[PDB]
Image (cartoon, rainbow, N blue to C red; front, side):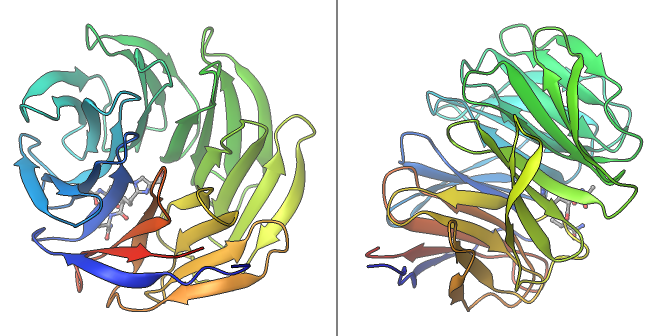
Length: 305
Ligand SMILES: CC(=O)N[C@@H](C)C(=O)N[C@@H](CCCc1ncc(CO)[nH]1)C(=O)N[C@H](C(N)=O)C(C)C
């Protein structure tokens, strides 16, 4: 149909503090969740079946991300480290040390030979996956780094910060290519590249999402109607059915917009706290959503469209 009809299929309980992030494995089999409870949990994407707990961080986790081959995870923790995990064994392969404050955000490149991280220490770091060594420290921002993401060929990194900036970095040199958003305020709470790498989706803590043309440095679309003044809420491109933008909201709902028209096409009700994180299944019309401390659950929603 022209609009989605997402309906609740499963509620995934087990975290003992706020959930911080959910991400589907690229092969579609798994959902990974991270939590302030210091744990990663792995769940079946299709039936919500609890698979395993992955443990080792000494403080809460803000983010987790999958390698391209679905075999590895990287997590970002308040313990000032990232950890690379073998999903099959649950073992920590590498501990990435160098940040001087909470690690907030992380991602693999498409090649999955590099990890990018952002920290409360106001830096972006680029790490070698094989050795766990820090290759580059970028003095990226002047306040905590809220998001980091590689583009589809891995040649670019986009970063965002509470300093109000969005910057694009040349991966190879670590040098800045452009400052896409250059305001004192509001905080830029989330950024990522579009699937094709031509656009950047950016959240600001004034209840606004924007789709930017990277090359032209111009705003193409604005999405509003949700509540986002405090938390670094993820946003997604939904591409399996209709072309949507998806985001959590501080009114405890999942918002779904038509990417082209900017109209709200669905609001998913059921969580009892802020929806901090949403993820879109790579092949099926499935959304995962996760909520803060009142709720501490993940919900799986399925649409015909
Ligand atoms: C472990 C922890 O909570 N660390 C502090 C520093 C924190 O505030 N982390 C944030 C992480 C939000 C999720 C996120 N990761 C990456 C993005 C976008 O790139 N968004 C938070 O709101 N935590 C919640 C809070 N402060 O209430 C909960 C999960 C404790």
